[PDB]
Each structure stands twice: as C-alpha cells, then as structure tokens.
Image 1: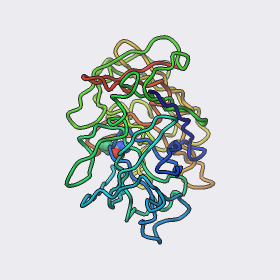
Image 2: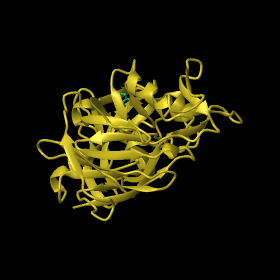
Image 3: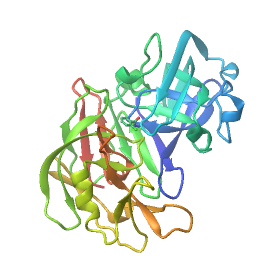
Length: 330
Ligand SMILES: NNC(=O)c1ccccc1Cl
C-alpha cells in the first residue's frame, strides 16, 4: 500500500505545516502537525478541558463506531519549546492520504498548554520519530508509520515541505518526479529515538564549504534550523546589523537586509537553503527588526534540522531494518 497527503503551512511564515488525517468511523478529519521529532499521535477531543479549546476541530470518540478505550492507558508529553499536553487513549482507524491503519493509538487530550490552545489551526500532532519515544503508559504504543510499515510497498515515508506553499507527505514510495538529481543517503542513529544523522559541513552564501561533522535531528515539527553557536555566528556575521538579542531570544536582523543562502552537507552532496527561507519577519507587528531562521542550539542539547532546512530538500525517512535518511535538491 501507499499514501499521499498534501501538507499546508499554517501561516505566512511557514511556522508549521498541517496535514489532514481521517480518524474513526465515519471519518472525522483533523489537521495534524506531522512531527518527525516525536512519537505520539494526539488530538484535541471532546475530552479536552473546554477552556483550552479555541477553534480547533475535535475528535469525539463516542461518535466513532471503531473507537475503543485503551483501558488504563494515559499519556503526557512535553516538547522542546516548553509546550505540553496529556490525556487518555483510544484505538481507532486512522487514514492518511489513502493509507489506512486499524488499531492505531489515538491519544485524546484532556489538557493542553496555552501555546496549543492559542493555535487554532493545529488539531493535534502525528509523531513520526521512533516508537521508543512514545509516552503512553503503562503500555507504550506504536507510531502510525510503525503500524503501517509492513503493509507499505517500501518501508519509507518522504517529506516534501513547501516554501510559502503546499507540499507533500508520501508513505510507502519515493516520487522520482519530486526532486532533481540524486538522493544522497546518510546513516541514522536511533539511540535517542530520533532521525539523528551527521551533516558533513556548511557554507554561508557563496563562501567556501567548511568540512565539519554536525550531529543533529531531522525534525519536521520544529520551525527553525538550530546549529552550533560557531556556525550560527559565522552565518549572521554576513548580515549587516544582525545581532543576538537576549530580550528577543535569538538572532535578529534589519528587515531591509538581503539574507545570504546557507548550505549544508549530506555526504558529498549539498543542500542550499535560499536566503529568503531564513527570514521569519518582524519580531512584533510593525517592527523593522526581523527574526532569523537560523538560531543557536546551545542550551537545547541537540542540533535540529527543522523546517527551514528540510523544506529546501526532498527528504526520505527510510525505515528499513537499519534506518537511513536521504536528501535530494528539488
Ligand atoms: N518536534 N521536535 C521535538 O519534539 C524535539 C525533539 C528533541 C529536541 C527538541 C525538540 Cl523541540
């Protein structure tokens, strides 16, 4: 089997992407944030504290004839940005772009943190990291990909995120018309539960490539590109007036600037992030200070190849017995 679904930016900055997901019988369609950096499929629901719901579409398990309470199971997750959610668990039928999993754990939120409430466009998350990170207790549950894998034509999914435009998540096949040149594959460590890999280096604008190993995660659920302070300093040094602002919480730059591109290495291959992809707009409405899309990972504890990097590529998440990651230009 295969599936194919369009993923759409939630706003004009590409802060996140939502993908429609069918849950239950009859289908209830929710728009979920596909997150290769976590491993829980959770949704706003009829059980979510009413004051914490503000415009989201909810899943109502009592209206699904295929929903079954997973007795005794709870979940609770905290994300790197400080947000969180928790609740109980149903199993139900879940379909993405024509690909159906029966008995998928659907984690129903009883509580969500303010950042989730405040984002009316995201109805939940669909985790696509390794199932070892799943938070369901006392019996850990598998991700949608994990459950689907055996049935897929090939045990893979791909992320093709758009810049200020829709893109695609495919399951079970590689669309050879969706990228240019070849896909370069690189080793993955699953030891931390992530799609963790090592970039071979970077360049800033038309500058020379610096060969250096950068270990990080391919994370569709993180907006920006978080890299070591040395790398980030070298980038922003090429932008007149750019500076790190402790009060804003990262590098900012004059909105009048033209940003240089940023290149990252995948083996001997190179992915070029255009300068425009690194502009996250005014820090506050009407400001002439703009927020940068490349930020330091110092104090996160891990480098994160978030949407800013991933949307510059066609990305293969290869879930073969030894997982790998593939990157192509597009
Ligand atoms: N979607 N990404 C995550 O949940 C994550 C994983 C590891 C470190 C930091 C973060 Cl923000």
